[PDB]
Length: 77
Ligand SMILES: [Zn+2]
Ligand SMILES: [Zn+2]
Image (cartoon, rainbow, N blue to C red; front, side, top):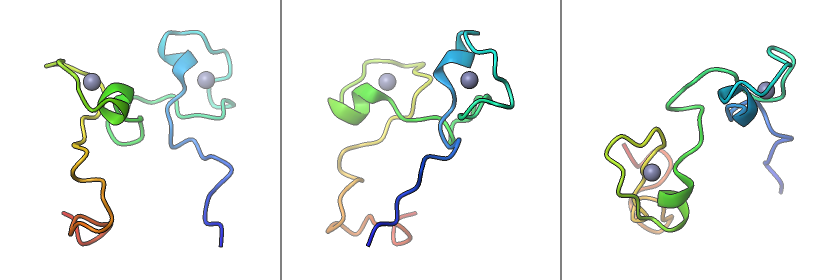
């Protein structure tokens, strides 16, 4: 039924980024800047509108996050 997860380090620590973490390898999140591991643009992910040309966040269209559509897990490129 449930295929979730406690919450791996998939996400990059938000404290370490601004140098506000003293855990390092002990932290519960990733301390490496990855365009994949890091989360998407809360704005483009929520509002779906970001006028940023150099946004350090991921910009995904709200038209590629639908099940029905042919853009699914594998089906999608
Ligand atoms: Zn941390
Ligand atoms: Zn953005």
